[PDB]
Length: 337
Ligand SMILES: O=S([O-])[O-]
Ligand SMILES: O=S([O-])[O-]
Ligand SMILES: O=S([O-])[O-]
Ligand SMILES: O=S([O-])[O-]
Image (cartoon, rainbow, N blue to C red):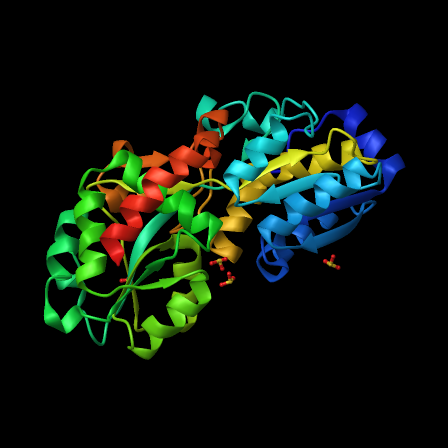
């Protein structure tokens, strides 16, 4: 009674194909509960989940296509600019998902590509070193905290010159909030350590070598929290940037119909519910109940209007323009060094 909306013609064509090839940036052990639940709904589809770096998904999909090859049926990546680039250059199958009827216009590239998540950039901190009542929830507050000599060497954030997703998050921050400029000069004052990888930043927070990290995903934070009780999460109340992992179907899928079923599943309440609950990835669908959900995010930040979703839109391709990147990175490098 929670099966996704399904074209019966699409289900029947997927019975015949019997195969689904995914290229995904989402760790298989996060995706596993979705793949297993999907296989239980459509036990007649054999799935090949390829768990890849976001740059590799792009480089690989572009070669197989250009060499004329059988490539993925479905592409699922947190690299929003690369997905929106492919989907706006002839790589995407147009499909109107029946589970996406209430997606906002800024969560879908028309019928080319869909948001599957709404993941906040948050603050994480080590409760042994910073109590919750002293962790500020505004950029101005963080900039003040980072003047304190006890915080020198105790801050982590992204290196937006080595992490594509860190670029996207810090750039959205810089474009939307003037107080980001104050904060970035404070990263400089505090000698912030910059990380290309969430894992290496968290390791240092958990050890107490950093006390606080800025701009990492809520989904990852919650996942680490489940096993690490010293890990605190604070949500920004002056304004929160959110990432949307983007899914689209290969225009040239050998199994377009199996990809349609999987895409519909990912967007369905059943799939988004299971994602929130098992993977602790923050859902896109507003009707999901639990901690990793739009409703929970909106209450934590003090209202929906305090979340700026990075849109599933060609507008974000300005992030790939050399002069646009340059202005941000020159401000960034002057501020944090
Ligand atoms: O779930 S694994 O077998 O693709
Ligand atoms: O770029 S490495 O840190 O994933
Ligand atoms: O690439 S993420 O793990 O920082
Ligand atoms: O208190 S925990 O949500 O950081």
